[PDB]
Length: 50
Length: 155
Image 1 (cartoon, rainbow over the protein chains, first blue to last red):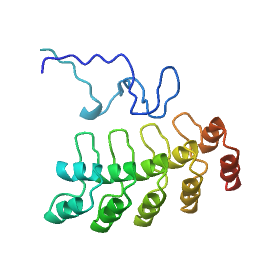
Image 2 (cartoon, rainbow over the protein chains, first blue to last red):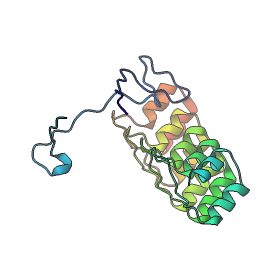
Image 3 (spheres, rainbow over the protein chains, first blue to last red):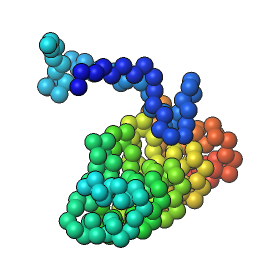
Image 4 (cartoon, chains in turn brown, purple):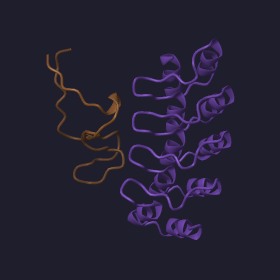
């Protein structure tokens, strides 16, 4: 509660370092956003403020 | 639920037998979606896999990344886990988020017997990943001549 997730790097599970190499378990950074042209609420983005 | 997962992670036979005979769900998972069969195929507990399949565990375990028990069977190099799971009726062309087929993992991990036993099931040699590469490309990246020969023989 009241914390920021700022992860400017990539995962490594237990074995494979992924420092500039294609790691099969290192995954990859955050996936992008699918701004679909005209679809349902599952693809209808919303903008919110607090 | 969590007790079964922890006991499976600990490699316990009678404990999991009693727990799943008590009435606990066979497909209990954490928020990351780790099934007991997932850990069973991870750590190579043959009796655990046998007990789960006899009691009716899920054959299509789906975690956050999309890994399957047969995926870890090919990754870790476990002999009879993949055999019993394919006897259950496991899919051979399951694609995870990375699009890595179990055959690709087995080829890249140097498990010739796993590659062959999946090939007997009707494995798709012409399967492609998210980058368009096949098991042959990963194998030649890994520099396995015999694996390349056995993969090209059925292609």
